[PDB]
Image (tube, rainbow, N blue to C red; front, side):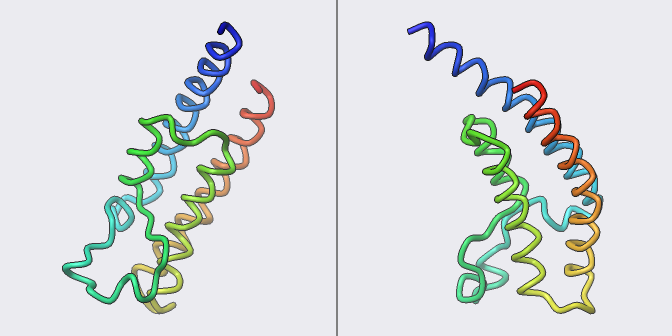
Length: 121
């Protein structure tokens, strides 16, 4: 149907805006601490701690399959990146501190992304 096409075009356009949001967030991680999944070979206990691992590569795979239907879904995954790191790692660690900085800086970007998603529809 034409209605299904129109919905698909909205999803595609949301995908474009989320790709740009994703790029901007990832630039706030120049150390590349959050670039890839935590390795279970190198942190064998990880899944005993963290039930839903997340990372920027995994988000990028979902994004390219148009797997985020709305901004809320994408923000949920971004928050997992931060929240997981802040639980597994102590306050005095480079990992924890990197997450705090990513969260603080990412807030700015997400604030205007929400306006854009509402504004454009």
